[PDB]
Image: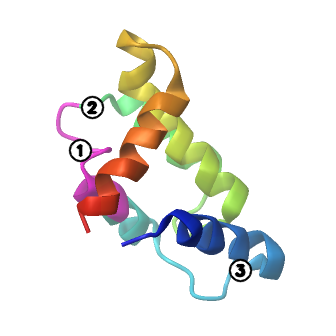
Amino acid sequence: NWDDADVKKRWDAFTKFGAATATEMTGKNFDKWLKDAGVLDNKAITGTMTGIAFSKVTGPKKKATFDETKKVLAFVAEDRARQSKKPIQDELDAITEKLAKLE
């Protein structure tokens, strides 16, 4: 459960410390964070937005850091949010709000 403040804490940490290779999570593990959350299903969602997101944010298969992470989360949220509603922030708040109770 990423708390309101905790979300900022865990995100911010990446920039403050520069946690590239310091508790790094493989692309598989980050992909897990996405698919298990229900945001990036990779089932009905586009391959365009999702694939290019990873290809842009991380590059290799290992991981990245804060900026790259906020990029991809935005791209994934934007995927379906922007099609119907358009504002990406709406679905990000939704994601954050969903996973708040979705453990």
Q: Mark 3: which amino acid?
A: Ala
Q: Kindly identify which residue carries mark 1.
A: 41
Q: Kindly identify which residue carries mark 2.
A: 45
Quadrant holding the N terminus: bottom left
- For the residues bearing labels 2 and 1, Cβ distance under 8 angstroms: yes
Which comes before the other along the chain, label 3 or label 1?
A: 3
Q: Would you say 13 lies left or right of 72 here?
A: right
Residue at horizontal 38 percent and vertical 46 percent from the top: 95
Cα–Cα gap, marks 2 and 1:
6 Å
Q: Do we see residue 16 in this rendering?
A: yes
Q: Kindly identify which residue carries mark 3.
A: 19
Q: Would you say 30 lies left or right of 55 here?
A: left
Residue 77 screen position, x and y as percent: 44, 35
- Dot 1 lies on which element? loop
- In magenta segment, residue 21: no
Relative depth, front residue between 80 and 91: 91
Q: Is residue 26 above or below residue 48?
A: below
Q: Which residues are magenta?
A: 33-44
